Length: 154
Ligand SMILES: Cc1cccc(/C=N/c2ccccc2/N=C/c2cccc(C)c2O)c1O
Ligand SMILES: [Fe+3]
Image 1 (cartoon, rainbow, N blue to C red):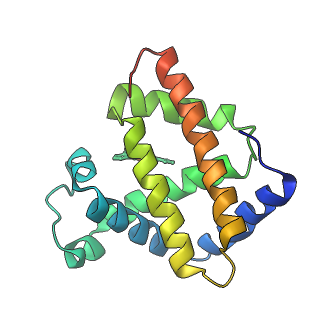
Image 2: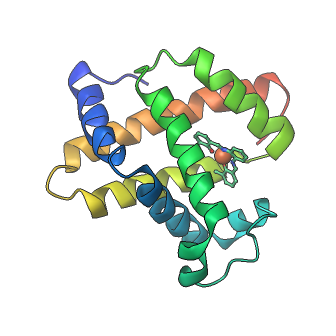
Image 3: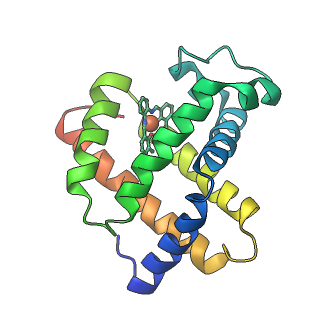
Protein backbone atom coordinates (compact mmCIF):
# COMPACT_ATOMS: atom_id res chain seq x y z
CA UNK A 1 0.00 0.00 0.00
CA UNK A 2 1.12 3.53 -0.86
CA UNK A 3 -0.65 6.90 -0.78
CA UNK A 4 0.58 10.05 -2.50
CA UNK A 5 1.34 13.06 -0.30
CA UNK A 6 -1.76 14.62 -1.81
CA UNK A 7 -3.83 11.65 -0.68
CA UNK A 8 -2.37 11.80 2.83
CA UNK A 9 -3.34 15.46 2.93
CA UNK A 10 -6.92 14.58 1.98
CA UNK A 11 -6.93 12.10 4.88
CA UNK A 12 -5.49 14.60 7.37
CA UNK A 13 -7.75 17.38 6.13
CA UNK A 14 -10.92 15.42 6.85
CA UNK A 15 -9.49 14.15 10.14
CA UNK A 16 -9.08 17.74 11.31
CA UNK A 17 -12.87 17.94 10.95
CA UNK A 18 -13.33 14.72 12.88
CA UNK A 19 -11.27 16.33 15.64
CA UNK A 20 -13.76 19.18 16.00
CA UNK A 21 -16.26 16.64 17.37
CA UNK A 22 -14.48 13.40 18.23
CA UNK A 23 -17.19 12.06 20.54
CA UNK A 24 -19.93 12.71 17.99
CA UNK A 25 -18.07 11.00 15.15
CA UNK A 26 -17.20 8.14 17.48
CA UNK A 27 -20.84 7.55 18.41
CA UNK A 28 -21.98 7.67 14.80
CA UNK A 29 -19.24 5.25 13.75
CA UNK A 30 -19.86 2.66 16.48
CA UNK A 31 -23.65 2.87 16.06
CA UNK A 32 -23.17 2.28 12.32
CA UNK A 33 -20.86 -0.65 13.08
CA UNK A 34 -23.24 -2.25 15.58
CA UNK A 35 -26.32 -1.79 13.38
CA UNK A 36 -24.47 -3.11 10.30
CA UNK A 37 -22.84 -6.06 12.08
CA UNK A 38 -24.62 -6.88 15.41
CA UNK A 39 -22.10 -9.62 16.27
CA UNK A 40 -19.38 -7.02 16.91
CA UNK A 41 -21.40 -5.69 19.84
CA UNK A 42 -20.82 -8.99 21.66
CA UNK A 43 -17.21 -7.94 22.24
CA UNK A 44 -18.21 -5.25 24.74
CA UNK A 45 -19.50 -6.68 28.03
CA UNK A 46 -20.05 -3.13 29.28
CA UNK A 47 -22.75 -2.30 26.74
CA UNK A 48 -23.41 -5.45 24.71
CA UNK A 49 -26.91 -5.16 26.15
CA UNK A 50 -27.52 -2.07 24.01
CA UNK A 51 -30.28 -2.60 21.46
CA UNK A 52 -31.99 0.52 20.11
CA UNK A 53 -30.15 3.47 18.59
CA UNK A 54 -31.57 5.57 21.43
CA UNK A 55 -29.85 3.33 23.99
CA UNK A 56 -26.62 3.50 22.00
CA UNK A 57 -26.78 7.31 21.79
CA UNK A 58 -27.34 7.53 25.54
CA UNK A 59 -24.50 5.17 26.46
CA UNK A 60 -21.50 6.74 28.18
CA UNK A 61 -19.51 3.54 27.63
CA UNK A 62 -20.15 3.60 23.89
CA UNK A 63 -19.25 7.29 23.70
CA UNK A 64 -16.05 6.77 25.67
CA UNK A 65 -14.99 3.88 23.47
CA UNK A 66 -15.60 5.92 20.33
CA UNK A 67 -13.22 8.56 21.68
CA UNK A 68 -10.59 5.92 22.46
CA UNK A 69 -10.85 4.43 18.98
CA UNK A 70 -10.67 7.74 17.10
CA UNK A 71 -7.90 9.12 19.28
CA UNK A 72 -5.81 6.04 18.62
CA UNK A 73 -6.64 5.96 14.92
CA UNK A 74 -5.89 9.66 14.54
CA UNK A 75 -2.44 9.16 16.04
CA UNK A 76 -1.73 6.40 13.52
CA UNK A 77 -3.06 8.30 10.50
CA UNK A 78 -0.93 11.36 11.22
CA UNK A 79 2.18 9.19 10.87
CA UNK A 80 1.30 8.74 7.19
CA UNK A 81 2.34 5.09 7.07
CA UNK A 82 5.29 5.27 9.48
CA UNK A 83 3.17 4.00 12.36
CA UNK A 84 5.04 0.94 13.63
CA UNK A 85 5.47 2.45 17.11
CA UNK A 86 1.77 3.26 17.47
CA UNK A 87 0.44 0.19 15.67
CA UNK A 88 2.40 -2.58 17.42
CA UNK A 89 0.69 -2.15 20.82
CA UNK A 90 -2.74 -1.90 19.20
CA UNK A 91 -2.15 -5.11 17.23
CA UNK A 92 -0.85 -7.19 20.13
CA UNK A 93 -3.71 -5.99 22.33
CA UNK A 94 -6.38 -6.82 19.75
CA UNK A 95 -4.92 -10.26 19.10
CA UNK A 96 -4.14 -11.54 22.61
CA UNK A 97 -6.45 -9.52 24.85
CA UNK A 98 -9.50 -8.55 22.79
CA UNK A 99 -9.27 -11.19 20.04
CA UNK A 100 -10.64 -8.96 17.29
CA UNK A 101 -10.82 -10.66 13.86
CA UNK A 102 -9.51 -8.84 10.79
CA UNK A 103 -13.04 -8.97 9.40
CA UNK A 104 -14.18 -6.78 12.31
CA UNK A 105 -11.50 -4.23 11.42
CA UNK A 106 -12.91 -4.29 7.89
CA UNK A 107 -16.40 -3.58 9.27
CA UNK A 108 -15.30 -0.60 11.33
CA UNK A 109 -13.37 0.75 8.34
CA UNK A 110 -16.64 0.67 6.37
CA UNK A 111 -18.42 2.56 9.16
CA UNK A 112 -15.69 5.22 9.33
CA UNK A 113 -15.89 5.88 5.59
CA UNK A 114 -19.69 6.02 5.70
CA UNK A 115 -19.85 8.48 8.59
CA UNK A 116 -17.16 10.77 7.20
CA UNK A 117 -19.11 10.93 3.95
CA UNK A 118 -22.41 11.53 5.74
CA UNK A 119 -21.05 14.35 7.92
CA UNK A 120 -18.69 15.97 5.40
CA UNK A 121 -20.23 15.38 1.92
CA UNK A 122 -19.12 18.71 0.49
CA UNK A 123 -15.48 17.73 0.95
CA UNK A 124 -15.23 13.96 1.51
CA UNK A 125 -15.64 13.04 -2.15
CA UNK A 126 -14.38 10.17 -4.28
CA UNK A 127 -10.73 11.25 -3.96
CA UNK A 128 -10.83 11.58 -0.18
CA UNK A 129 -12.83 8.37 0.25
CA UNK A 130 -10.35 6.53 -1.93
CA UNK A 131 -7.46 7.94 0.08
CA UNK A 132 -9.05 7.00 3.40
CA UNK A 133 -9.84 3.54 2.04
CA UNK A 134 -6.16 3.02 1.17
CA UNK A 135 -5.07 4.39 4.55
CA UNK A 136 -7.34 2.05 6.47
CA UNK A 137 -6.34 -0.82 4.19
CA UNK A 138 -2.67 -0.18 5.00
CA UNK A 139 -3.67 -0.01 8.67
CA UNK A 140 -5.42 -3.39 8.44
CA UNK A 141 -2.65 -5.07 6.44
CA UNK A 142 -0.04 -3.99 8.99
CA UNK A 143 -2.21 -5.18 11.89
CA UNK A 144 -2.72 -8.50 10.08
CA UNK A 145 1.05 -8.84 9.78
CA UNK A 146 1.49 -8.45 13.54
CA UNK A 147 -1.38 -10.88 14.10
CA UNK A 148 0.21 -13.55 11.91
CA UNK A 149 3.54 -12.91 13.65
CA UNK A 150 1.97 -13.83 16.99
CA UNK A 151 0.10 -16.75 15.45
CA UNK A 152 -3.29 -15.08 15.84
CA UNK A 153 -5.36 -15.97 12.78
CA UNK A 154 -7.73 -13.10 13.21
C1 LIG B 1 -9.42 0.61 14.98
C2 LIG B 1 -8.95 1.10 16.31
C3 LIG B 1 -8.10 2.21 16.35
C4 LIG B 1 -7.63 2.70 17.55
C5 LIG B 1 -8.00 2.09 18.74
C6 LIG B 1 -8.83 0.99 18.76
C7 LIG B 1 -9.18 0.37 20.01
N1 LIG B 1 -9.75 -0.78 20.16
C8 LIG B 1 -10.06 -1.33 21.46
C9 LIG B 1 -9.51 -0.84 22.65
C10 LIG B 1 -9.82 -1.43 23.88
C11 LIG B 1 -10.69 -2.53 23.92
C12 LIG B 1 -11.24 -3.01 22.72
C13 LIG B 1 -10.93 -2.42 21.49
N2 LIG B 1 -11.54 -2.82 20.25
C14 LIG B 1 -12.55 -3.63 20.21
C15 LIG B 1 -13.26 -4.08 19.03
C16 LIG B 1 -14.45 -4.78 19.16
C17 LIG B 1 -15.21 -5.13 18.05
C18 LIG B 1 -14.78 -4.77 16.78
C19 LIG B 1 -13.59 -4.07 16.60
C20 LIG B 1 -13.19 -3.68 15.21
C21 LIG B 1 -12.83 -3.73 17.71
O1 LIG B 1 -11.64 -3.09 17.49
C22 LIG B 1 -9.31 0.49 17.51
O2 LIG B 1 -10.15 -0.61 17.45
FE1 LIG C 1 -10.68 -2.01 18.66
